[PDB]
């Protein structure tokens, strides 16, 4: 599904911000 | 038909199992569990915003957890954990009690081999901040 | 040393889910949960020592839950619930986590359509007796 | 063996049949 792909890309991006907000 | 017998059973087993696992957590793992609770609490609001953005399947959340765990960081693993925790809050009776345990299975099954050492070092950093 | 990540996550999700379900339980369903609590304690020791009477993964307990729910009774259904809970007590690590999810699935999947009404009147009757 | 599980299941059923009446009595 195209929508799911873009949704997970937004969640993967949230995950990355959580990594960067530690350092 | 006065009670949802499955929901009542799910509550009993869920709490007993929650305490059973917490009982057997080492001191170090108890620290990580409290760090995970804070980490998941920080990402909760951003997570609900993205999900609400695209608001309407049990495969959908399973697909998101899988994408988040696609070879991954501690931040994405925590986001996947909190997504499962929020689906658990919506899947609270009847036929929804099946999709939750399967969703958790996807989480644990798709974890990377290095999950233990990655999250151990990351959640410890969470303890430093908070 | 290092942590068992999967055990940390399971502990978190299990509690968060337990709190969620409890929150959404109707009042009449919350009284039954208490009744299920006490009724599960009375069957615990007879259950455990019967398990110790024989034997000493998911296959055997699942086979017992299935045998207890074979068209059944509130007492048998509650005995099945406590069996799952006791297996959860010793299934707290790794692949054991899976055996618990598969066991609980047998329980909920094999409940009879009558359970909602039969356990509603039974668990409520137990609550009045133990009051 | 599998027949041992057959015997144990009957024992838990008896416990179940007893719990059914015991908790509504007295
Ligand atoms: Mg991305
Ligand atoms: Mg964030
Ligand atoms: Mg009705
Ligand atoms: Mg009704
Ligand atoms: Mg009614
Ligand atoms: Mg444990
Ligand atoms: Mg242990
Ligand atoms: Mg916690
Ligand atoms: Mg939290
Ligand atoms: Mg959706
Ligand atoms: Mg829908
Ligand atoms: Mg849905
Ligand atoms: Mg599909
Ligand atoms: Mg999908
Ligand atoms: Mg890829
Ligand atoms: Mg990627
Ligand atoms: Mg990668
Ligand atoms: Mg990876
Ligand atoms: Mg179903
Ligand atoms: Mg499934
Ligand atoms: Mg692992
Ligand atoms: Mg560690
Ligand atoms: Mg070690
Ligand atoms: Mg070491
Ligand atoms: Mg709650
Ligand atoms: Mg409530
Ligand atoms: Mg076995
Ligand atoms: Mg197996
Ligand atoms: Mg069966
Ligand atoms: Mg029958
Ligand atoms: Mg029978
Ligand atoms: Mg009978
Ligand atoms: Mg117990
Ligand atoms: Mg193992
Ligand atoms: Mg079936
Ligand atoms: Mg079925
Ligand atoms: Mg009552
Ligand atoms: Mg055998
Ligand atoms: Mg025997
Ligand atoms: Mg006997
Ligand atoms: Mg009595």
Image (cartoon, coloured by chain):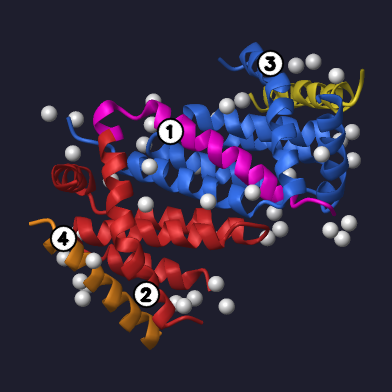
Chain colours: A orange, B red, C blue, D yellow
Tell me: is circle 1 under 8 Å from ligand 6. Answer: yes
| Residue identified by numbered label 2 | B49
User: Furthest residue to the bottom?
Assistant: A2
Disc 3 crowd rating (10 Å Cα; few below 14, some 14-19, many 20+) is some
- Depth check, front residue: C87 or B16: B16
Name the disc covering residue B21, or none. Answer: 1
Marks 3 and 2, Cα distance to the nearest angstrom? 51 Å
Which residue is painted at 26% across and 66% down in the image? Answer: B70
Of all chains, the one bearing label 4 is A
Marks 3 and 4, Cα distance to the nearest angstrom? 50 Å
Instruction: Give ligand 4's quarter of the image.
Output: bottom right
Residues in magenta?
B1-30
| Residue identified by numbered label 3 | C50
Q: Nearer the viewer, mark 1 or mark 4?
A: 4
Left or right: B117 in relation to C18: left
| C60 is higher (above) or lower (below) than D15 | below
């Amino acid at each position: 599904d195209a929508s799911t792909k873009k949704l997970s890309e937004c969640l993967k991006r949230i995950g990355d911000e959580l990594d960067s907000n530690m350092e | 038909d006065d009670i949802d017998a499955s929901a009542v059973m799910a509550a009993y087993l869920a709490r007993e199992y929650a305490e059973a696992v917490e009982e057997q957590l080492t001191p170090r793992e108890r620290d990580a569990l409290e760090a995970l609770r804070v980490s998941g609490e920080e990402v909760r609001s951003p997570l609900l915003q993205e999900l609400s953005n695209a608001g309407e399947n049990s495969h959908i959340p399973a697909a998101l957890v899988s994408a988040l765990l696609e070879a991954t960081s501690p931040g994405r693993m925590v986001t996947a954990v909190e997504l499962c925790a929020q689906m658990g809050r919506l899947w609270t009776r009847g036929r929804q009690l099946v999709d939750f345990m399967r969703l958790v299975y996807v989480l644990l099954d798709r974890l990377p081999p290095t999950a233990d050492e990655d999250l151990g070092a990351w959640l410890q950093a969470v303890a430093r901040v908070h």
